[PDB]
Image 1 (cartoon, rainbow, N blue to C red):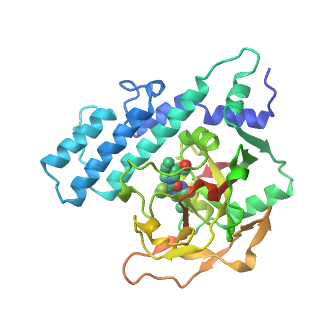
Image 2 (cartoon, rainbow, N blue to C red):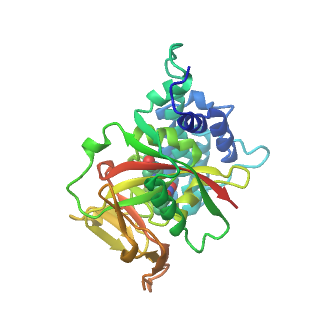
Image 3 (cartoon, rainbow, N blue to C red):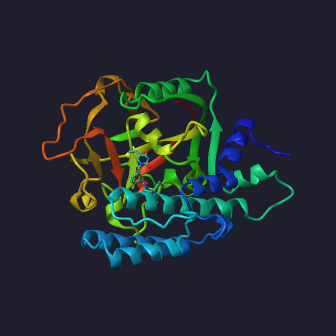
Length: 349
Ligand SMILES: CCc1cn(Cc2ccc(F)c(C(=O)N3CCN(CC)[C@H](CCO)C3)c2)c(=O)[nH]c1=O
């Protein structure tokens, strides 16, 4: 006897699909049989991070021989992969390391989803109502003719980046987000409050909606995070939407809009994993892109600057090396974040 609005019922059914998570983890080659997702613990995942840090130590020492082979073998033993007939590959590039961190990140958010969906049943409540209660996060659908829908649609469409031309986006539905406790934790005192994008894999939304956006743990290798262990946002919808990792066959995903208390940004042209130690008073890191929304179109929504598009050149160019195409924003404390809107997005490849 579900008491939820049907749109919220659809949302819960989408993000609590444990079998869809199983599929995604198999595409990342995690062995869903040898280590079932229902048999996932924080300790298993912590040991995996510690193995990745040992791998990082080998990479920074230029040790691509025995020491790296066994450090990788230890990671693959603690986090079982199914490579079928092939031999597990060595991890020595930053991207190869990053791919394994992303795998561990999905496991951590799936672990939260498993505890939630397997949590104590009722028989008095519809299952979706139980799962929704166990989120401790209000999800309120907004009317498609509403003003909020119009401005979010404009933000989504007007900040789609030109270099992301292989797909367009259609807003299927829109929910207001109010996670228990975030208002009382939020740094209302800080300036430069912006409504910014965050995209994530479908496996992670139960954890994100339940536990909020959070920092990478200390046991994670620092070089996996280009601007340090923070929470990353964009002002271009498509740059965040790329981190949904939607596909031709799985072209439905979610995008998150959050009020971000940026304060004073430490501006940077290129990546630095140690950027948090460079704050020294400032409250956020801004990686500078060559294209960004301009102030002329900025609007305001419940106290936050919505950086509506179109985007234009910023004259930013890094002579030292590589230049970011688009901005990214990083805060290092979740009390600078308040989740606001959840977009159900169709990817039209
Ligand atoms: C620029 C927009 C953008 C970037 N990136 C990539 C990225 C890179 C490094 C990062 F540290 C994080 C990040 O924020 N993390 C790390 C993982 N998790 C650790 C517990 C958390 C997840 C939220 O709880 C916090 C994200 C996305 O994935 N989506 C996006 O929209």
